[PDB]
Amino acid sequence: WKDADTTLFCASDAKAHETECHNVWATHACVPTDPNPQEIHLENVTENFNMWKNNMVEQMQEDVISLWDQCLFDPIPIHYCTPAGYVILKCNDKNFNGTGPCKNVSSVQCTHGIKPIKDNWRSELYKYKVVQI
Amino acid sequence: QVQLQESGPGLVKPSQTLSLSCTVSGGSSSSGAHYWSWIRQYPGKGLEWIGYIHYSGNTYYNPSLKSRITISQHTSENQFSLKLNSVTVADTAVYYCARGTRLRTLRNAFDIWGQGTMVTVSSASTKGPSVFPLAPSSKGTAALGCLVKDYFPEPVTVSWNSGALTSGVHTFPAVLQSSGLYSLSSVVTVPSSSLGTQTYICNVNHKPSNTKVDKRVEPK
Amino acid sequence: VLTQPPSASGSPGQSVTISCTGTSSDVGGYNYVSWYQHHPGKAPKLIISEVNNRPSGVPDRFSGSKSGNTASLTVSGLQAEDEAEYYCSSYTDIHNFVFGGGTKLTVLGQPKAAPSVTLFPPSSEELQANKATLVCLISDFYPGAVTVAWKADSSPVKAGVETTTPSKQSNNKYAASSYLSLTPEQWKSHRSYSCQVTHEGSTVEKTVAP
Image (cartoon, rainbow over all chains, first blue to last red):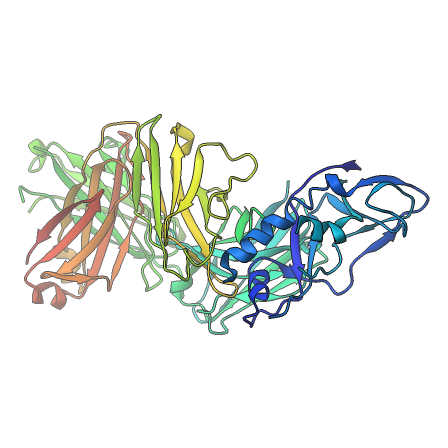
């Protein structure tokens, strides 16, 4: 793979039928969540992450803009995912801080379900990285 | 690379049930978080969203189709399909399949389209045309024609004075009436210098019904 | 359900703008307006997405916008390859979409010409055979983008009407045809019959009587 930058999409379990502010945004912005995502253990290999250079903390926050844009009470989980030809590498190291080496990586299709401030995103982002197949 | 190929019938009888199939080929189908949509263009008019279905199996039809409609998927053979019921001549259109995206910067747009496939609704079995003339007079240039009305199916061929007269000639696209029958015009502009003098004949030709009509066109 | 103008023209080099009027729940309720370029017999190309976003491989010179409920697409610096038909769509409500009628962008390659309207009455032969059709012939005009309407006496009609889409002549100019079918009683009950064609804000109108 190459470590690269691409246009992501969002997915949620939002209800089409109802008025809670960003249920309303998500129904017009995101797709439904697949109840069984893929999680593939990296055998053996290690890669270098950098929460500070992650252009998922660059597209997130632009969707948070359009969220409030039309917004004006409970948040639900939103997932961020990659298109064909790309995939998300996830760091499973427990004393990982955000940067440097990470021996236990795995690949995921979408991120975890995120409660909704760049720093609040990075509080959960840290372990995610995009590469191109 | 990912293109969309629509297959299906050209003709269907009224009250029946059109069903078209679209084959993805690049390229994902099931694989992606896109939406797989059906859109028809009434040539001119003219453009209308039918519905789509998501990789998760979620269907979203147009509200104005009171249960005349279902859409479904073959995760397997990377293809999907629409089944439109109880069709009338109204449903005559070009049908495009298209990929709807919910990526950011492309949200609720249709990035990939299909080249389109023409679908015609009509009861009619093969019928030969009625060739009616369109006369000039002084009611310099004059202009006269042949109305080739009520035939099926297409095509029809016109030519004036056995192909000798080519200059000033124009034949129109055929036009499907609510009946289910076609109709077209052929017309030529001329030196009215020669209306009592030069004879003018259109040579209609309808191979489907093995009919050939040659109509005299003259003044008053 | 959205509203565009039929034609829109400019000469090579110039800049052209195209409206697309909606309602507060169509456009102006969502930032999901799209624009599609459709060359004939070919698959439509998406060119603007989410109001003003050029996809990859779409030139710098196409641009979107919306004021209130009227989205708008601009083409800066025309070239021959831009001559096509352009549609706009907007998301609307829980999963639904609306389109405009389409706009013919003609990149002017020759003098504009107003349409010549010849309106043939039903022939003897056809009348004697029970039926009657009025043939509007529209000829020698440019750009190739018109609109026809019919009138009985001076009342508008759309029952029993079919129309050609503008087609090129041997002299690189455009032609089109509209038909009005009716029973001969309808023909000689009404005082007169009018075919009127709108070509770029002008409106020519021929009339025949029994």
